[PDB]
Amino acid sequence: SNTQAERSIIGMIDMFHKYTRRDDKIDKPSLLTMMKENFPNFLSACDKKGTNYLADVFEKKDKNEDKKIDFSEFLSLLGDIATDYHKQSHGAAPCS
Amino acid sequence: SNTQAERSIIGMIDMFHKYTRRDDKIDKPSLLTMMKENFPNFLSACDKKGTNYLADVFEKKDKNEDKKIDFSEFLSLLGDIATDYHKQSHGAAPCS
Ligand SMILES: O=S(=O)(O)c1ccc2cc(N=C3C=CCC=C3)ccc2c1
Ligand SMILES: O=S(=O)(O)c1ccc2cc(N=C3C=CCC=C3)ccc2c1
Ligand SMILES: [Ca+2]
Ligand SMILES: [Ca+2]
Ligand SMILES: [Zn+2]
Ligand SMILES: [Zn+2]
């Protein structure tokens, strides 16, 4: 009875919870695994452009420098991926 | 060949573009239609709790007060919906 958009939001929370530790936050090796497992085509587009997105993603998104990615910082990471796909839809190259 | 997570991000951009005007932004009646069409179960949970989420969503999310919701403000709206589902998964009531 949920719509495609509601299922996508619910699945986003469930995806976060595949990778969290017991403090409900994602550490660095688990964040890189999450990216490889869930955004491999995005990552491959970046590599084609000469960008290794995994070299700096944790440092860029761990905004409070606690060495963990909490749910708010995870939303910001999904917002960056979504913003790259929105620029592509307007004719930008991937991973711009 | 895209994963479920990549399909969800792509579908999010496509959903934004169902509702934009020619300036790539969503006006107020189209934002309310988008919510009714895409998040009806979320909305129904809010109504059960006595909250009419559509009364104030535009005013809360139009952060630069230009009377349009641009892609950045649309991501913030999806982040609020996702944060409510993340609190529910931790045992909060819906639409808290
Ligand atoms: O046709 S599919 O490629 O299988 C597809 C997948 C997910 C979608 C998410 C959509 N909406 C979202 C809402 C909130 C967060 C992410 C996507 C809309 C359409 C979608 C379509
Ligand atoms: O089994 S389903 O209910 O049909 C489903 C639907 C969408 C998902 C999105 C997922 N990941 C997302 C990534 C980015 C933005 C939104 C969701 C993960 C699992 C999902 C599962
Ligand atoms: Ca952090
Ligand atoms: Ca605005
Ligand atoms: Zn959690
Ligand atoms: Zn656009």
Image: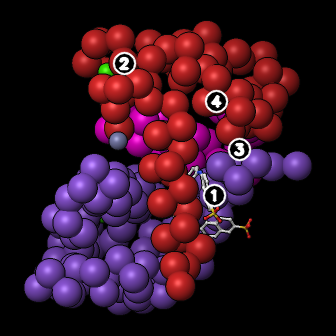
Chain colours: A purple, B red
Q: Earlier in the sequence, mark 2 or mark 3?
A: 2
Q: Of all residues shown, which one is farthest toward the left?
A: A50
Identify which amino acid the numbered label 1 is placed on. Ser
Q: Which mark is residue B54?
A: none
Say which of B81 and A26 sits in front.
B81
Q: Would you name the residue on which mark 1 appears?
A: A8
Kindly identify which chain the residue marked by label 3 belongs to.
B
The answer to whether dots 2 and 3 both sit on one chain is: yes
Q: Secondary structure at mark 2?
A: loop
Residue B92's tag is 3
Residue at 44%, 30% (x, y): give it: B20
Camera sees residue A21: no
Cα gap from disc 4 to disc 3, whole angstroms: 22 Å
Q: Are marks 4 and 2 on the same chain?
A: yes
Instruction: Note whether B45 is above or below B2 in the view shown.
Output: above
Q: Of residues A38 and B49, which is closer to you in this image?
A: A38
Q: Residue furthest right?
A: A1
In magenta, the rendered stretch is B72-96
Residue in view at x 42 percent, y 35 percent: B74
Q: Is A78 contained in the magenta span? A: no
> What is the quadrant of the C terminus of chain A in the image?
bottom left
Disc 2: host chain: B
Q: Which residue is mark 2?
A: B68
Do pointers 2 and 1 mark residues of a single chain?
no
